[PDB]
Amino acid sequence: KNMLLGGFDTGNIKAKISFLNEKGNIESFAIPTVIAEAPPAKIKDEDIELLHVRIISNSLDGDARSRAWYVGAYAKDQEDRQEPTVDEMSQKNKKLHLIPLFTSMAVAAARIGKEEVSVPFSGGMPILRGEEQILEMLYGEHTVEFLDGTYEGKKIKITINDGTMNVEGVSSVLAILFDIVNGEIVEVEGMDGESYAINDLGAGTSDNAFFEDGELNKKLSTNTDLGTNKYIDEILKNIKERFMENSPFKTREDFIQRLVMPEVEKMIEDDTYKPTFSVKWGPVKENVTDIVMDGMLKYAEDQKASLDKFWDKTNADKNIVVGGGVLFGYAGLRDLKEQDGFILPKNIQESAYFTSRSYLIANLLEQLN
Ligand SMILES: Nc1ncnc2c1ncn2[C@@H]1O[C@H](COP(=O)(O)OP(=O)(O)OP(=O)(O)O)[C@@H](O)[C@H]1O
Ligand SMILES: [Mg+2]
Protein backbone atom coordinates (compact mmCIF):
# COMPACT_ATOMS: atom_id res chain seq x y z
CA LYS A 1 0.00 0.00 0.00
CA ASN A 2 1.56 3.24 -1.24
CA MET A 3 -0.78 5.49 0.68
CA LEU A 4 0.22 8.42 2.87
CA LEU A 5 -2.59 9.47 5.14
CA GLY A 6 -2.54 12.99 6.52
CA GLY A 7 -4.40 16.04 7.76
CA PHE A 8 -3.17 19.35 6.32
CA ASP A 9 -3.66 22.60 8.24
CA THR A 10 -2.18 25.38 6.14
CA GLY A 11 -2.01 28.91 7.44
CA ASN A 12 0.23 31.86 6.67
CA ILE A 13 2.55 31.42 9.60
CA LYS A 14 3.06 27.69 8.92
CA ALA A 15 1.95 24.64 7.00
CA LYS A 16 1.02 21.96 9.52
CA ILE A 17 0.69 18.23 8.80
CA SER A 18 -0.43 15.27 10.94
CA PHE A 19 0.02 11.84 9.32
CA LEU A 20 0.21 8.13 10.16
CA ASN A 21 3.76 6.86 10.37
CA GLU A 22 4.77 3.23 9.75
CA LYS A 23 3.86 2.47 13.36
CA GLY A 24 0.29 3.66 12.66
CA ASN A 25 0.69 6.59 15.01
CA ILE A 26 0.17 10.30 14.49
CA GLU A 27 3.33 12.27 13.74
CA SER A 28 3.08 16.01 13.35
CA PHE A 29 5.34 18.79 12.11
CA ALA A 30 5.20 22.30 10.62
CA ILE A 31 6.91 24.03 7.73
CA PRO A 32 7.11 27.87 7.86
CA THR A 33 5.26 29.37 4.91
CA VAL A 34 8.38 30.69 3.20
CA ILE A 35 9.94 29.81 -0.16
CA ALA A 36 12.89 31.17 -2.16
CA GLU A 37 14.22 30.45 -5.64
CA ALA A 38 17.12 27.96 -5.59
CA PRO A 39 19.73 26.67 -8.09
CA PRO A 40 19.32 23.26 -9.84
CA ALA A 41 21.79 21.69 -7.34
CA LYS A 42 23.38 22.19 -3.90
CA ILE A 43 26.57 23.71 -2.51
CA LYS A 44 13.11 16.56 16.68
CA ASP A 45 12.28 17.49 13.05
CA GLU A 46 15.88 17.98 11.95
CA ASP A 47 14.89 16.72 8.49
CA ILE A 48 13.03 19.95 7.79
CA GLU A 49 15.88 22.16 8.97
CA LEU A 50 17.35 22.19 5.45
CA LEU A 51 14.90 21.83 2.58
CA HIS A 52 16.29 22.35 -0.91
CA VAL A 53 13.87 20.73 -3.36
CA ARG A 54 13.06 20.36 -7.00
CA ILE A 55 9.31 20.28 -7.54
CA ILE A 56 7.57 19.29 -10.75
CA SER A 57 3.84 19.93 -10.84
CA ASN A 58 1.26 21.24 -13.27
CA SER A 59 -0.16 23.03 -10.24
CA LEU A 60 2.68 25.49 -10.83
CA ASP A 61 3.23 27.70 -13.84
CA GLY A 62 6.03 29.56 -15.53
CA ASP A 63 8.99 30.32 -13.35
CA ALA A 64 7.67 27.71 -11.03
CA ARG A 65 6.72 24.67 -13.05
CA SER A 66 9.89 22.62 -12.77
CA ARG A 67 12.61 24.25 -10.76
CA ALA A 68 14.34 24.20 -7.36
CA TRP A 69 13.45 25.94 -4.10
CA TYR A 70 14.48 26.47 -0.56
CA VAL A 71 11.45 25.93 1.71
CA GLY A 72 10.61 26.55 5.33
CA ALA A 73 13.24 27.56 7.86
CA TYR A 74 16.13 27.14 5.41
CA ALA A 75 14.52 29.78 3.22
CA LYS A 76 13.90 32.28 6.03
CA ASP A 77 17.55 33.31 5.62
CA GLN A 78 17.62 33.77 1.85
CA GLU A 79 17.74 37.44 0.79
CA ASP A 80 15.19 36.88 -1.94
CA ARG A 81 12.75 34.92 0.14
CA GLN A 82 9.09 35.21 -0.49
CA GLU A 83 6.69 35.45 2.36
CA PRO A 84 2.97 36.10 2.50
CA THR A 85 2.37 39.82 2.20
CA VAL A 86 -0.33 40.98 4.60
CA ASP A 87 -2.21 44.30 4.48
CA GLU A 88 -1.58 47.45 6.53
CA MET A 89 -4.96 46.29 7.84
CA SER A 90 -3.84 32.96 -5.58
CA GLN A 91 -2.09 33.15 -8.88
CA LYS A 92 0.96 34.76 -7.58
CA ASN A 93 0.77 33.39 -4.09
CA LYS A 94 -0.33 29.96 -4.82
CA LYS A 95 3.16 28.66 -5.02
CA LEU A 96 3.89 30.14 -1.64
CA HIS A 97 1.36 27.73 -0.17
CA LEU A 98 1.51 24.82 -2.60
CA ILE A 99 5.29 24.34 -2.31
CA PRO A 100 5.46 24.08 1.46
CA LEU A 101 2.34 21.82 1.25
CA PHE A 102 3.92 19.41 -1.29
CA THR A 103 7.21 19.56 0.58
CA SER A 104 5.48 18.45 3.76
CA MET A 105 4.02 15.64 1.67
CA ALA A 106 7.41 14.62 0.36
CA VAL A 107 8.92 14.78 3.84
CA ALA A 108 6.26 12.55 5.40
CA ALA A 109 6.77 10.02 2.58
CA ALA A 110 10.52 10.09 3.15
CA ARG A 111 9.76 9.66 6.81
CA ILE A 112 7.95 6.38 6.05
CA GLY A 113 10.49 5.12 3.53
CA LYS A 114 8.18 5.53 0.53
CA GLU A 115 8.76 7.24 -2.82
CA GLU A 116 5.42 6.62 -4.47
CA VAL A 117 2.50 7.99 -2.50
CA SER A 118 -1.16 8.50 -3.11
CA VAL A 119 -2.27 11.36 -0.90
CA PRO A 120 -5.98 11.68 -0.32
CA PHE A 121 -6.26 15.32 0.79
CA SER A 122 -7.85 16.29 4.12
CA GLY A 123 -7.83 20.06 4.61
CA GLY A 124 -9.78 23.11 5.68
CA MET A 125 -11.14 26.07 3.71
CA PRO A 126 -9.15 29.36 3.71
CA ILE A 127 -9.94 32.65 5.53
CA LEU A 128 -14.62 32.38 -5.04
CA ARG A 129 -12.61 29.29 -4.21
CA GLY A 130 -15.21 26.52 -3.80
CA GLU A 131 -14.27 23.27 -2.04
CA GLU A 132 -13.67 21.31 -5.26
CA GLN A 133 -11.96 24.32 -6.84
CA ILE A 134 -9.28 24.25 -4.17
CA LEU A 135 -9.04 20.49 -4.67
CA GLU A 136 -8.63 20.76 -8.44
CA MET A 137 -5.53 22.88 -7.93
CA LEU A 138 -4.02 19.88 -6.06
CA TYR A 139 -5.10 16.94 -8.17
CA GLY A 140 -2.65 14.95 -10.24
CA GLU A 141 1.03 14.22 -9.98
CA HIS A 142 3.81 16.21 -8.33
CA THR A 143 7.43 15.15 -7.87
CA VAL A 144 9.61 16.47 -5.08
CA GLU A 145 13.32 15.84 -5.30
CA PHE A 146 15.58 16.49 -2.32
CA LEU A 147 18.73 18.16 -3.57
CA ASP A 148 20.16 18.37 -0.07
CA GLY A 149 19.48 17.69 3.59
CA THR A 150 18.72 14.33 5.13
CA TYR A 151 16.97 13.00 2.04
CA GLU A 152 19.33 14.19 -0.72
CA GLY A 153 18.77 12.06 -3.79
CA LYS A 154 15.25 10.95 -2.91
CA LYS A 155 12.47 11.64 -5.42
CA ILE A 156 8.88 11.51 -4.19
CA LYS A 157 5.95 10.68 -6.46
CA ILE A 158 2.91 12.38 -4.92
CA THR A 159 -0.44 11.53 -6.47
CA ILE A 160 -3.55 13.35 -5.33
CA ASN A 161 -6.90 12.14 -6.75
CA ASP A 162 -9.48 13.00 -4.12
CA GLY A 163 -10.11 15.01 -0.95
CA THR A 164 -12.40 16.96 1.39
CA MET A 165 -12.12 20.47 2.78
CA ASN A 166 -14.15 19.50 5.76
CA VAL A 167 -16.37 22.41 4.92
CA GLU A 168 -19.30 22.67 6.89
CA GLY A 169 -18.18 19.40 8.54
CA VAL A 170 -17.71 18.46 12.10
CA SER A 171 -14.45 16.99 11.12
CA SER A 172 -13.08 20.02 12.89
CA VAL A 173 -13.77 18.70 16.41
CA LEU A 174 -12.66 15.09 15.89
CA ALA A 175 -9.27 15.50 17.64
CA ILE A 176 -11.10 16.29 20.93
CA LEU A 177 -12.83 12.94 20.77
CA PHE A 178 -10.37 10.55 19.07
CA ASP A 179 -6.73 9.57 18.77
CA ILE A 180 -5.00 7.29 16.32
CA VAL A 181 -2.94 4.48 17.71
CA ASN A 182 -2.69 2.24 14.65
CA GLY A 183 -6.47 2.38 14.74
CA GLU A 184 -9.10 4.71 16.14
CA ILE A 185 -9.26 4.97 19.85
CA VAL A 186 -11.75 6.98 21.85
CA GLU A 187 -10.12 9.49 24.18
CA VAL A 188 -10.74 9.18 27.83
CA GLU A 189 -12.33 12.58 28.69
CA GLY A 190 -14.68 15.03 27.18
CA MET A 191 -17.31 14.87 28.98
CA ASP A 192 -19.20 15.60 25.77
CA GLY A 193 -23.20 19.06 22.81
CA GLU A 194 -25.46 20.35 20.05
CA SER A 195 -23.68 23.64 20.47
CA TYR A 196 -19.98 24.09 20.92
CA ALA A 197 -17.32 26.64 20.15
CA ILE A 198 -13.89 25.74 18.86
CA ASN A 199 -11.37 28.43 19.69
CA ASP A 200 -8.12 27.79 17.87
CA LEU A 201 -5.57 30.08 19.51
CA GLY A 202 -2.81 30.66 16.95
CA ALA A 203 0.44 32.55 16.31
CA GLY A 204 -1.07 35.53 14.43
CA THR A 205 -4.77 34.75 14.69
CA SER A 206 -7.46 33.47 16.98
CA ASP A 207 -10.09 31.42 15.18
CA ASN A 208 -13.39 31.63 17.06
CA ALA A 209 -15.71 29.09 15.43
CA PHE A 210 -19.23 28.17 16.50
CA PHE A 211 -21.12 24.97 15.80
CA GLU A 212 -24.82 24.30 15.84
CA ASP A 213 -25.85 20.77 14.93
CA GLY A 214 -22.16 20.35 14.28
CA GLU A 215 -22.31 22.61 11.23
CA LEU A 216 -20.61 26.00 11.27
CA ASN A 217 -22.74 29.05 12.03
CA LYS A 218 -21.05 31.44 9.55
CA LYS A 219 -22.50 34.54 11.18
CA LEU A 220 -21.30 34.28 14.79
CA SER A 221 -18.08 32.40 13.92
CA THR A 222 -15.20 34.84 13.50
CA ASN A 223 -11.39 35.18 13.17
CA THR A 224 -9.47 37.81 15.03
CA ASP A 225 -5.86 38.71 15.09
CA LEU A 226 -5.39 37.92 18.70
CA GLY A 227 -2.26 35.89 18.23
CA THR A 228 0.54 35.00 20.50
CA ASN A 229 3.11 36.71 18.29
CA LYS A 230 2.49 40.21 19.59
CA TYR A 231 2.90 39.07 23.21
CA ILE A 232 5.98 37.10 22.22
CA ASP A 233 7.37 40.22 20.55
CA GLU A 234 6.82 42.22 23.72
CA ILE A 235 8.54 39.59 25.88
CA LEU A 236 11.54 39.47 23.57
CA LYS A 237 11.83 43.25 23.62
CA ASN A 238 11.94 43.37 27.42
CA ILE A 239 14.52 40.57 27.58
CA LYS A 240 16.82 42.48 25.22
CA GLU A 241 16.27 45.62 27.30
CA ARG A 242 17.32 43.84 30.52
CA PHE A 243 20.47 42.58 28.84
CA MET A 244 21.14 46.20 27.96
CA GLU A 245 22.52 47.23 31.32
CA ASN A 246 26.01 45.80 31.68
CA SER A 247 19.03 39.55 20.00
CA PRO A 248 19.37 36.33 22.10
CA PHE A 249 17.01 34.38 19.77
CA LYS A 250 16.72 34.10 15.95
CA THR A 251 13.02 33.57 15.28
CA ARG A 252 10.02 33.37 17.58
CA GLU A 253 10.08 29.60 17.13
CA ASP A 254 13.61 29.53 18.49
CA PHE A 255 12.32 31.44 21.51
CA ILE A 256 9.42 29.00 21.78
CA GLN A 257 11.45 25.86 21.16
CA ARG A 258 14.49 26.37 23.29
CA LEU A 259 13.34 28.73 26.06
CA VAL A 260 9.63 28.20 26.52
CA MET A 261 8.54 24.68 25.49
CA PRO A 262 10.56 22.70 28.06
CA GLU A 263 9.20 24.79 30.94
CA VAL A 264 5.64 24.35 29.67
CA GLU A 265 6.14 20.59 29.28
CA LYS A 266 7.15 20.35 32.95
CA MET A 267 4.25 22.53 34.07
CA ILE A 268 1.82 20.25 32.29
CA GLU A 269 2.96 17.01 33.91
CA ASP A 270 3.33 18.52 37.36
CA ASP A 271 0.84 21.11 38.61
CA THR A 272 3.27 22.22 41.32
CA TYR A 273 6.25 23.00 39.09
CA LYS A 274 7.09 26.72 39.26
CA PRO A 275 8.85 27.56 35.93
CA THR A 276 12.09 29.49 35.46
CA PHE A 277 13.36 31.14 32.28
CA SER A 278 16.97 31.83 31.71
CA VAL A 279 18.57 33.35 28.66
CA LYS A 280 22.24 33.10 27.76
CA TRP A 281 23.45 36.02 25.73
CA GLY A 282 27.13 36.86 25.14
CA PRO A 283 29.06 36.72 28.44
CA VAL A 284 25.86 37.20 30.47
CA LYS A 285 23.11 34.93 31.79
CA GLU A 286 19.89 36.63 32.92
CA ASN A 287 16.95 35.16 34.78
CA VAL A 288 14.01 36.51 32.80
CA THR A 289 11.24 34.50 34.51
CA ASP A 290 9.14 37.51 35.57
CA ILE A 291 9.42 38.97 32.05
CA VAL A 292 8.34 35.77 30.36
CA MET A 293 5.57 35.05 32.84
CA ASP A 294 4.16 38.59 32.61
CA GLY A 295 3.74 38.14 28.86
CA MET A 296 2.07 34.75 29.19
CA LEU A 297 -0.27 35.91 31.89
CA LYS A 298 -1.26 39.04 30.01
CA TYR A 299 -1.99 36.78 27.05
CA ALA A 300 -3.92 34.22 29.07
CA GLU A 301 -6.02 37.00 30.57
CA ASP A 302 -6.66 38.67 27.24
CA GLN A 303 -7.73 35.28 25.86
CA LYS A 304 -9.92 34.59 28.93
CA ALA A 305 -11.77 37.80 28.11
CA SER A 306 -12.03 36.99 24.43
CA LEU A 307 -13.36 33.51 25.18
CA ASP A 308 -16.08 34.85 27.55
CA LYS A 309 -17.14 37.51 25.07
CA PHE A 310 -17.49 34.76 22.41
CA TRP A 311 -19.24 32.50 24.90
CA ASP A 312 -21.98 35.12 25.48
CA LYS A 313 -22.22 35.93 21.78
CA THR A 314 -23.01 32.27 21.03
CA ASN A 315 -24.16 30.89 24.40
CA ALA A 316 -22.57 27.67 23.41
CA ASP A 317 -22.98 24.65 25.71
CA LYS A 318 -19.27 23.85 25.57
CA ASN A 319 -16.26 25.90 24.57
CA ILE A 320 -13.37 23.83 23.26
CA VAL A 321 -10.02 25.66 23.39
CA VAL A 322 -7.10 24.45 21.22
CA GLY A 323 -4.05 25.67 19.28
CA GLY A 324 -0.57 26.59 20.39
CA GLY A 325 -1.84 29.52 22.45
CA VAL A 326 -3.12 27.02 25.03
CA LEU A 327 0.49 25.91 25.58
CA PHE A 328 2.12 29.31 25.30
CA GLY A 329 -0.27 30.81 27.83
CA TYR A 330 -0.80 27.55 29.75
CA ALA A 331 0.28 29.28 32.97
CA GLY A 332 -3.02 31.14 33.12
CA LEU A 333 -5.14 29.18 30.67
CA ARG A 334 -4.91 25.90 32.58
CA ASP A 335 -7.47 27.51 34.90
CA LEU A 336 -9.99 26.66 32.17
CA LYS A 337 -9.60 23.00 33.16
CA GLU A 338 -11.72 24.02 36.16
CA GLN A 339 -14.64 25.89 34.58
CA ASP A 340 -17.78 24.14 33.33
CA GLY A 341 -18.31 25.51 29.84
CA PHE A 342 -14.68 24.95 28.79
CA ILE A 343 -13.04 21.86 27.34
CA LEU A 344 -9.26 21.64 26.84
CA PRO A 345 -7.73 18.67 25.08
CA LYS A 346 -6.64 16.06 27.64
CA ASN A 347 -3.48 15.41 25.63
CA ILE A 348 -2.56 19.06 25.91
CA GLN A 349 0.90 18.65 24.31
CA GLU A 350 -0.76 17.95 20.96
CA SER A 351 -2.86 21.11 21.24
CA ALA A 352 -1.09 23.02 18.46
CA TYR A 353 -1.78 20.20 15.97
CA PHE A 354 -5.44 19.91 16.94
CA THR A 355 -6.90 20.95 13.60
CA SER A 356 -4.43 18.88 11.51
CA ARG A 357 -5.10 15.95 13.84
CA SER A 358 -8.87 16.36 13.28
CA TYR A 359 -8.42 16.36 9.52
CA LEU A 360 -6.18 13.27 9.75
CA ILE A 361 -8.75 11.42 11.79
CA ALA A 362 -11.45 12.60 9.35
CA ASN A 363 -9.33 11.26 6.55
CA LEU A 364 -8.94 7.82 8.15
CA LEU A 365 -12.75 7.50 8.59
CA GLU A 366 -13.20 8.38 4.93
CA GLN A 367 -10.87 5.54 3.97
CA LEU A 368 -12.84 3.17 6.20
CA ASN A 369 -15.94 4.47 4.34
N1 LIG B 1 4.51 23.32 23.42
C1 LIG B 1 4.42 24.67 23.33
N2 LIG B 1 4.76 25.46 24.36
C2 LIG B 1 4.66 26.81 24.27
N3 LIG B 1 4.23 27.47 23.19
C3 LIG B 1 3.86 26.78 22.08
C4 LIG B 1 3.94 25.31 22.09
N4 LIG B 1 3.51 24.89 20.89
C5 LIG B 1 3.20 26.00 20.16
N5 LIG B 1 3.40 27.12 20.87
C6 LIG B 1 3.16 28.50 20.42
O1 LIG B 1 1.75 28.74 20.35
C7 LIG B 1 1.51 29.77 19.37
C8 LIG B 1 0.47 29.34 18.35
O2 LIG B 1 0.89 28.10 17.78
P1 LIG B 1 0.06 27.47 16.56
O3 LIG B 1 0.81 26.29 15.96
O4 LIG B 1 -1.37 27.32 16.98
O5 LIG B 1 0.06 28.69 15.52
P2 LIG B 1 -0.44 28.56 13.99
O6 LIG B 1 -1.56 27.56 13.80
O7 LIG B 1 0.82 28.53 13.16
O8 LIG B 1 -1.06 30.04 14.00
P3 LIG B 1 -2.09 30.66 12.93
O9 LIG B 1 -3.44 30.32 13.53
O10 LIG B 1 -1.76 32.14 12.96
O11 LIG B 1 -1.76 29.95 11.63
C9 LIG B 1 2.82 30.02 18.66
O12 LIG B 1 3.39 31.22 19.17
C10 LIG B 1 3.66 28.81 19.02
O13 LIG B 1 5.06 29.09 18.93
MG1 LIG C 1 -3.54 28.15 13.40
Image (cartoon, grey):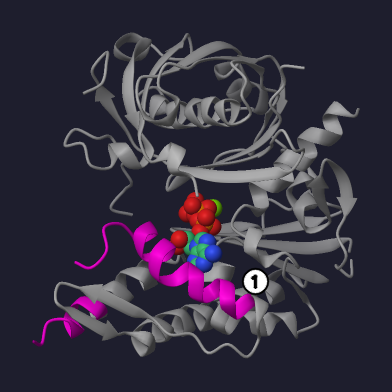
Where residue 30 appears, as percent x and y from the top left, is 50, 44
Q: Residue at x 49, y 13 (%)?
A: 143
Identify the residue shown where x is 28% and y is 34%.
Answer: 82
* Residue wearing tag 1: 310
Most foreground residue, 206 or 351: 351
The image quadrant of residue 360 is: top right
Q: As rendered, which of 80 and 158 lies closer to the eye?
A: 158
| Highlighted range, magenta | 239-268
Quadrant containing the N terminus is top right
Q: Residue 128, image x and y in percent?
A: 55, 28
Count the numbered circles shown. 1
State which quadrant residue 132 falls in: top right
User: In which quadrant will I find the C terminus?
Assistant: top right
Q: Can residue 94 be seen in this view?
A: yes
Report the front residue among 295 and 149: 149
Residue at image coords 48%, 58%: 205
Q: Main secondary structure of the magenta part?
A: helix
Identity, as a three-letter code, of the amino acid under mark 1:
Phe
Asked whether residue 242 is drawn in magenta, I would say yes
Instruction: Choose top left, top right, bottom left or bottom right for residue 254.
Output: bottom left
Asked if 162 appears above or below 230 in the picture, the reply is above
| Label 1 C-beta lies within 8 Å of the nearest ligand 1 atom | no
**Residue 305 visible in rendering:** no
- Above or below, comparing residue 305 to residue 10 in the picture: below
Q: Relative to 192, is 323 on the left or the right?
A: left
Query: Where residue 241 appears, x then y in whole percent?
Result: 17, 81
- Label 1: which secondary element: helix
Pick whichever, 39 or 148, lies toward us: 148
Q: Is residue 90 magenta?
A: no
Spot occupied by residue 17 in the image (x, y as percentages of width and height): 59, 40
Instruction: Residue lying at the far left in this picture: please name it.
Output: 246
Horizontal side of residue 179 vs 368, given as left or right: left
